[PDB]
Image (spheres, coloured by chain):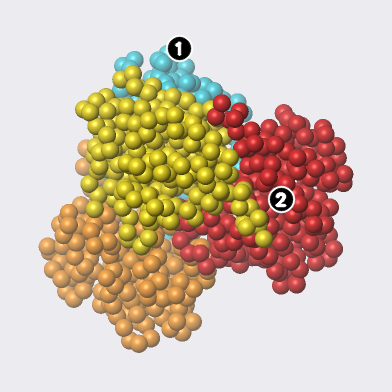
Chain colours: A red, B yellow, C cyan, D orange
Amino acid sequence: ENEILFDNGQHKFMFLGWEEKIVQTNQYLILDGNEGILLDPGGAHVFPRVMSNVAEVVDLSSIRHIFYTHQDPDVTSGILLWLSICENAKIYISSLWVRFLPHFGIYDQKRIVPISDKGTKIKLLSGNELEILPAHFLHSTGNFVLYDPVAKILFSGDIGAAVFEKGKRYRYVDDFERHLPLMEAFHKRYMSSNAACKKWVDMVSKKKIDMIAPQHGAVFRGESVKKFLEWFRNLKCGVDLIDNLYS
Amino acid sequence: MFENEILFDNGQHKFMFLGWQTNQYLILDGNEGILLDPGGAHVFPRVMSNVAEVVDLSSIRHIFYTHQDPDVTSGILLWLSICENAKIYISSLWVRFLPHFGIYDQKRIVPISDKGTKIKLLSGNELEILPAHFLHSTGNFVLYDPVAKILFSGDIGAAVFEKGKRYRYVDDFERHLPLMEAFHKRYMSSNAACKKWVDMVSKKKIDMIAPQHGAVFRGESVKKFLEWFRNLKCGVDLIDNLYS
Amino acid sequence: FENEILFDNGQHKFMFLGWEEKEEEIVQTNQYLILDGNEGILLDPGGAHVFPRVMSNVAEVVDLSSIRHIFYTHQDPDVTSGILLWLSICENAKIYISSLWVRFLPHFGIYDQKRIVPISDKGTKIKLLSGNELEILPAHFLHSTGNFVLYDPVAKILFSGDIGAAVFEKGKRYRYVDDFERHLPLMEAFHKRYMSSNAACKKWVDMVSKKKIDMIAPQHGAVFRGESVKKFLEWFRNLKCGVDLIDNLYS
Amino acid sequence: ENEILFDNGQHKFMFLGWEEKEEEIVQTNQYLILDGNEGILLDPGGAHVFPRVMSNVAEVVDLSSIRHIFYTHQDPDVTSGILLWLSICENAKIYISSLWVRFLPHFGIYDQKRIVPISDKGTKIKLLSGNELEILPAHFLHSTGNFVLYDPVAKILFSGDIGAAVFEKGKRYRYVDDFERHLPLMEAFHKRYMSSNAACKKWVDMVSKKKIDMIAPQHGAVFRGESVKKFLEWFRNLKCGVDLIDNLYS
């Protein structure tokens, strides 16, 4: 049941899945001209189905960029598979993490772009940009988000992640306050501090963002883009609550 | 080269630093062994061979991991399958990535709560697993051995050496400190987290601090590190310089 | 489609586990389980790809700590991924494998062989706590260099591995061979390409045909019962295969 | 370290160095054919030896000019390394027996846009220069689907496990210069693994039509000089496999 979150001729932003059946994980795909961009593609456990859902929309040889927000252990199993099935892809991972690439069968880094802490920009043959923005400590030590200025969509990874209730999945947040309880425990335990959340929001508030797309949970649209950014900005998380940790 | 080293010993309780970037530690107590962050699948044939060489692998009874991935999560199923009597200690935050590593039976998995726990040994001695979250991992722990008075600190106090110039002990803190500063400023989450950790840790007796990478703190360098780390501006404190 | 009982006398069951369909699909693999007293025996359990659900299907029938023997006919690449997984979830199991390959087990994460039983070329006997036995009989070159079948004298069932294996068509799977000649198109090409020689087929047929066999249970395909048991053994003994066709292979 | 087995300026056959100054496993040979500016790997090592085999190859040729990788049959480990080689040699096609391509998913191989499945009759790799490599049938010697590779320019037969030997503890050597002291390292494996004398004879008779300066096995030492014709005569009369089956069925 794929979905188009944006479409202008050169540029589609796609929300694939799901199935009927592990947490729920989302898969997103950007089509721009004759190249594809994978966002946090599924690791080895889910790999047969994610790859077929992908080959179903775009030639796997036209995948030209694969971006990883961070080193989840269930995405890290898949780097070598994606590398070996998408010969034309560069793989983008944080430079903090590239030393572990041998430990995954990656010994040649000629298609590995280690992202600097300040971030970077992917430029495509069409002439459109993707912005990989710093998002460190939310939650991983080296962590990034991806902003598509053509589509006006922020791929947030685990920022805005939610875990659904028992068989009550849904794809879009149209009522923020009823969505928040699926979010709150994860964000307080995992996000490093309110200082980190305020800095990240103050940065994403300068981009034109119609939709925030997390890696788990529902896609934020409409009025929940504002509401999530406010809630996140004032959130006490992580070290702010570290006396209840350790306790 | 790589003769083993004894950091503590009385006949009944030994704390060992194995030879060969990454350090390997082994606590022997009575007839139990305790592995501390043993190497993952790439180093496994000789790390496993080096341990079996000091202690029978069926008397390994506890394997402790400060935090998860990839230097060591390649190895959890291997250590599980070659140490039939071991319990594996890992943060509860990560135990449901365990299927994705072929670990489907969790009857020998001890998921550590955020407040930590204690390993009690048949001898009646204890090991204290103390919280160290956000230094650097979201779920992170250190191990305190009260008999030997040694803190196994994981990456807290880690150093990356120059060239082929590794050494085992920091006997001069200030000449060692530059090998530490970049890592700790980039990785440790905030000074608030370092200050909270030092204040709990400094209530214990610590003759040595043993990190997972780098040199072991002994002598007066143990106090110098705890005071330096307590005042360290790290991580989110430098976040406008991370960002740009 | 549920699990099925091929034999039961109170203390001894031979189980043919049901299929999930849920295609998959090519072709399906069978899982069998022998329960004797309070101990279980797995026959060629699936490797790592099928392992989560294969393991749950077994755990639903028997406590995995009661599995005490795991037998592999031969060294399919589908199963060697799972040897370490089964070792770790069946703490009391010894696994029986061919000695030709016991030295290459490190390449699959198996370094301690205190629960590895290397089967010599003669075969061996699994003795069960009750005092019943399973007989591991030689089946070398049908097809792999080191290969075995398992004969259950209590249940009168031969677990044949790949001998008698069949590949089903798209949506035409079925559990039992009640019409041998209709089953033959699903079997014949494989056996002619894989089984090494008619000389090997004759030796194996003459050995197994001295045992009392109500059913033949292969690792892929349908279970032979009734008249198909002796029809299959007769077909197999006269089969021209493998090196007997080597001028047609080479060309 | 690496060795040159043939050279005419434009065509080489390499016997790559090993290992490892000290022994590991009980180990294997790696071969490399250079023709024009394109490379051919012969049974490159699986994942455990992959860091070392990969760097040894990069020392002789850019991994981007590897265009053919040939596998005699499957094991693993050699099947452990296919995904690694596929991902490090962009331009290589992998040649494997058609019996074996169904196990490819179970090793992470999902898109066979770069898999060249060999039919039982064999095939010829045609190189850009116009030279060829002959993939010749060798089925049941020992594996069900099995092939050898013959290089007509270099006059070298890469034999896979045919002619394989396991060395004694710390007495490895690179060349068979005396067949008879080499034979004890070989015969138990061949009598147990090779399917029948009938299979050995057709293969020797097939192979005897080629000019063979040298037989290069995957384990053991390379046959040269008088060992070649000594090996082919021994292998031709060998009682193996099913011929010895009533000791296997007492």
Q: Amino acid at mark 1?
A: Gly
Residue A200: mark: 2
The chain that hosts pointer 2 is A
Q: Is residue D23 left or right of residue A131?
A: left
**Does residue B194 lie above or below C229 as drawn?**
below
Percent position of residue D240, x then y: 24, 53
**Residue C10's mark?**
1
Residue at 49% over, 73% down = D64
Q: Amino acid at mark 2?
A: Trp
Q: Is residue D69 left or right of residue A180?
A: left
User: Is disc 1 on the same chain as disc 2?
Assistant: no
Left or right, A160 with respect to C95, comes to: right
Q: Position of residue C145 (x, y in %)?
A: 33, 48
Judge by depth and name the residue closer to the eye, B125 or D147.
B125
Q: Residues within 10 Å of mark 1 (few under 14, many from 20)?
A: few
Please give the name of the residue rendered at 42% of the width and 33% of the height, measured from the top-left corner. Answer: B143
